[PDB]
Image: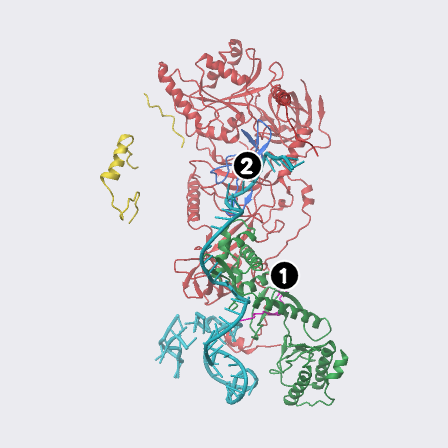
Amino acid sequence: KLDTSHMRYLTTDDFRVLQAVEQGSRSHEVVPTPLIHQISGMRSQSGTNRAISDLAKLSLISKMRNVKYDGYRLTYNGIDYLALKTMLNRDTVYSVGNTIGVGKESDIYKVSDKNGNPRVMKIHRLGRSNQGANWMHLSRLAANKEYQFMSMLYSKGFKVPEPFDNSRHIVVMELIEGYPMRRLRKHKNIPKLYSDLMCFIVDLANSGLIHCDFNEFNIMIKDKLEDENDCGFVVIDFPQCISIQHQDADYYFQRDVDCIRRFFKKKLKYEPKPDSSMLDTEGFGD
Amino acid sequence: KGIVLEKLGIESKQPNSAIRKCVRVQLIKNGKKVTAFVPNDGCLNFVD
Amino acid sequence: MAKVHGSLARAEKPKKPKGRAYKRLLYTRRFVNVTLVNGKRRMNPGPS
Amino acid sequence: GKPDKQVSKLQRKNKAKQLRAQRILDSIENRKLFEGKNGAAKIITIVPLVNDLDPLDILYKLLKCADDEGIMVQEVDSKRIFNVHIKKFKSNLKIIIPDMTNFLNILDCAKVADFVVFGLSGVQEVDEEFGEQIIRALELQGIASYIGVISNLSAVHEKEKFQLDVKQSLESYFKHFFPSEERVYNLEKNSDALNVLRTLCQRLPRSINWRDNRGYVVADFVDFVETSPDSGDLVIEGTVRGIGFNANRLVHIPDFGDFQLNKIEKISTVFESNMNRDTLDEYAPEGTEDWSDYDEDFEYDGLTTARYDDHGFLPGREQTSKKAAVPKGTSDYQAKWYLDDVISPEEEERQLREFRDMEKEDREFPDEIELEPSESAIERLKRYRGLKNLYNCDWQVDEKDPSSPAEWKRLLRIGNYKNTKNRIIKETKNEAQAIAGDRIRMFIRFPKFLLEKIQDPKQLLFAVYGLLLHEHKNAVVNFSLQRWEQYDKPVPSQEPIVVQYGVRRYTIQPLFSQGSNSPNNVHKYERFLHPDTVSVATCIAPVDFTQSPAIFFKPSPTDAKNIELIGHGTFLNADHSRILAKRAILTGHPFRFHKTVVTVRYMFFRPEDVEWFKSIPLFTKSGRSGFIKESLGTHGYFKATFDGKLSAQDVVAMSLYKRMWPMPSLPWNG
RNA sequence: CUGAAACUUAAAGGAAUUGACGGAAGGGCACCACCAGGAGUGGAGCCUGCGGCUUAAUUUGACGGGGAAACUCA
């Protein structure tokens, strides 16, 4: 797994050697000893051997010798570490870790900055390990496309939070002091939030984005004040989104409307007095 | 025979990092300048 | 290091024989007293 | 572009005759400094290496081959400095005798002389307590062309076959410290006296680089002109030697200090000191205006954690809402449960053996320090920083300190010394008003009260040494340091030690370190001198722009030679960017052992010491880094993790740094 | 067409022999894989194990016969 406490055991030369490993591993399949000795551009063999041994005993570089072919292999934790070093070069990550929520393909920790403000993170471990290149490359491109999705959702006035960076497949997000409806019990002004939550579906479908897994576990509700009870609705449906040009959007849309009416008729016992938003008006809206 | 000029801290990487403690020397008889290795000193405290 | 000026010839381990007696000592080291070590001829043996 | 060259035979002989034409031209122009009719000055210093020799006997034996009785008849009565002209080789000589009761006087004799002549005894062996250190100290202060010679070879048995074995013994001794020459010559032989007289007349002496790049005058006549009742004008009549003298640059006098010039007068033009004078101040007032932009005024009182926030934690906020509940008699736990709201020779030997105990423990445990349970490390370690790597962290020179000397702000800061010294030698060869080899009348602004300390110029020397631009101005400079042989006596980094670099001597308490090159120019402060290799010694001292060698001593008047010569070195650099920091090590024993976490014993004695020191990394003398885990016990017991698995024979160390600055300088007299 | 030199460099090259690697291909052959289902988990409360938080200690590894107020207790 990922144990982030071990990369501060490394010096400047150690992640210089790790940068040489990630530079040499993207040109060939397996990088041997002299390409790490030459691509790094550093003085001695001894320092390269010491840095490679430092990554080896921290289980970051796997030594492999398949019949007179010495070579080295990057694991998940080493590329997590070098992505967090090039995140440190962009002077924003400072102190990391409380595991809140373990997804299939993205695990959520709890981080901070130099300013000390509360933030979180999204790692991406595709396959969990028979490491090749397709798994980590596909995690990297998935993190990149959800970063452009994340910035496009934040840039258009939605109640979707602020992105910062897409440092390889390591995605650093703002913490939101928000509660799910598993924790939430009763609210004063339920029809106003129901109006906001059909209007969110309306302007997503006007934008052309169809969030499909729109269950009770999706909605994160921020409590800004305790005396006036200000609210904000955070929606996490990023890999399950589908475009408006797809052929199967109809039962997705009525499934979203049917789930929100059944969840608001189950817990809060509130019924929709206006009619349901159907697919064709939103189709002409985009 | 020569007269020394400078201190050359050349770094020379692969395969052995030689921390080169060597002296630029101006010769006497012809007036051109060659580099020159100083042997066996760990400190080069002798050829000032 | 620096010799005292009384080096005028006119007016610790035991020392090691030189010249012909050293050739005597090498002969009796190698062939008079042959050290049979592991089927071979080991010069300078350690603790073994 | 240009075609190939086919050099002919005639072009080759034109090449050879042109190179030898210009080369005989500048060899002659180097040899026309020594026109022995009027414009010549050769300096001979004859020093004998045993107590039982008289140097006037060596003078007698040398000049009996020149066949002039009347010069000696003048020279017997009461004279010590002589100006002998010879008609045998047509050269002008000036011969300097030393006073044997002062070592520094012999240093002053041979540091000005173009020839150093070493007298030797064929009867008594030379002293390993007097004459060896004469040889080594003159050797390390710089010698030109030298002559080695004997005078007691008649006092041994009169058969010459015994005498050549003595001559070979002197040759083997003199080869050990002077390998440029191989023959010890005899004054008892008349032809050998002719040979050594010929070599002292004709041969070009080699140039000592530091003294010939500032210009120096030896003085034959001293006179005084009264100008004010508190200060007047010295008159110096001598011959200028070196690069020359300018009326604006300052001039150093040995055993007197630095003085400022009034006017000059050549008799073989008259020049004066204009408005471009170098002021007689030790700190330049323009250096106050140089350090105008302070950057780091970081306070240490308002710090919850140590100064590791560039490489460690976040500042932790602890809003202490202390409310008191009063039932009569209550511990902290119940009060925490009630009001929670959520929104003199004896002294010398005494200091000798305590300091020798300090470097023997410093050799065994390098820089550790012990903590008692009674003493708390909170007020002890305010000013320390616990940076993980010394050679990667970002310090700065500009940071302030309440332990600052106030004259650090008024310091002369040179960016590149390499361009600066080449620049200062090129203008001090350019606008030299008087070139060398001229009889000069030199006038010195000089206070009246120091006139008792001068001597007769024909009984004692009067060496006059010029100094360069801003040489009187102080800076932080550096010196190399190598200890002398058979010297095992300790030196720490805070005792008064007088440095002889150049002709000035200055008492200093020098910082000791190792010259390992750093990317951020930080170095390890060592408490004592390293006994093995060449250490480095930086301090606050006046600057020297010729890379003169430095000899290090303290005056010890217990011996007849009233000097304890410590070591030697060379002026390396005048850099303010080179900074020093000590390392503090706090020892600790790993108590209990486990696959992941290690309990450490006897490190601190409080839990909040661990809480403050939660950021700083741990390292092992076996070569393993580590980090702390949780403050376990109330007696400073804490848990810690490591890179691997350690045994009971390893020790946990902890590095803390605080910045150390150099100490100022003062000149030494006597 | 004729045709260098300074300088730099311990290999450059020819034939031939094996094959880790394949995300080339083709077979098997599996409910720790799928289809046909069934029971479910993940949704609710509670017990336990790990992590986290706190502690003076939450001893502690990756089920440790590690069931549990003294003991086991480290």
Q: Chain of mark 2?
A: B
> Crowdedness of circle 2 by 10 Å Cα count: few (<14), some, many (20+)?
many
* Quadrant of residue A232 within the rendered picture: bottom right
Residue at image position (52%, 14%) is D75
Taking A166 as reference, is D665 above or below it?
above
Residue E5, x across and y down, in percent: 59, 34
Chain letter for the green colouring in the rendering: A
Residue at image position (40%, 20%) is D167
Residue D101, x across and y down, in percent: 48, 26
Q: Which mark is residue A91?
A: 1
Q: Specify whether residue D512 is in view.
A: no
Of the pair D214 and A127, the residue shown nearer to us = A127
Q: Which mark is residue B23?
A: 2
> Is residue D102 toward the left or the right of residue D90 in the image?
left
Residue D627, x across and y down, in percent: 49, 62
Q: Specify whether residue D594 is in view.
A: yes
> Is residue A164 toward the left or the right of residue A19 in the image?
right
Pointers 2 and 1 in contact (C-beta within 8 Å): no
